[PDB]
Amino acid sequence: VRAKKPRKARTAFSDHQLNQLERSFERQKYLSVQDRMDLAAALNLTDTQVKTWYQNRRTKWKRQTAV
DNA sequence: CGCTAATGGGTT
DNA sequence: AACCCATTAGCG
């Protein structure tokens, strides 16, 4: 049942990282490439981890908007 | 299970 | 390139 393609380990975000990602999201639902890279740098996260966090946060946000 | 990080497969 | 968003899957 295991994938043939290697998947990345699941990142566990710190409370500090989640607090800052949530503050960023409340302010701006979409980030410029520069604002995203800068946030990744400030939090010692990868660009992709921040990009994906934003994407999955927008999914969650759209589901709450629908109720 | 529930939440949500990462990925698939297609769109913008 | 980044997004959309259904899906796959890790873990408390």
Image: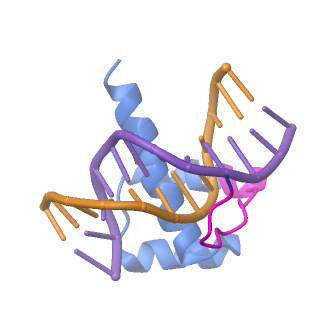
Chain colours: A blue, B orange, C purple
Dominant secondary structure of the magenta stretch? loop
Report x, y in % for residue B7: 52, 64
Left or right, A15 with reference to A1:
right
Q: Is residue A20 visible?
A: yes
Q: Which residue is drawn at 47% across and 66% down?
A: A51
Position of A64 relative to A43 (above/below): above
Q: Which residue is drawn at 77% across and 50% down?
A: A15
Position of B4 relative to B1 (above/below): below
Q: Residue at x 58, y 55 (%)?
A: A21
Q: Which residue is drawn at 41% across and 80% down?
A: A34
Left or right, B7 with reference to A67:
right
- Between C6 and A33, which is closer to the camera in this rendering? C6
Report x, y in % for residue B4: 61, 45
**Residue A10 on the magenta segment:** yes
Report x, y in % for residue C3: 30, 59
Quarter location, residue A35: bottom left
Position of A52 relative to A63 (above/below): below
**Which residues fall within the magenta stretch?**
A2-18
For the C terminus of chain A, which image quadrant?
A: top left
- Between A60 and C11, which is closer to the camera in this rendering? C11
Report x, y in % for residue A58: 40, 46
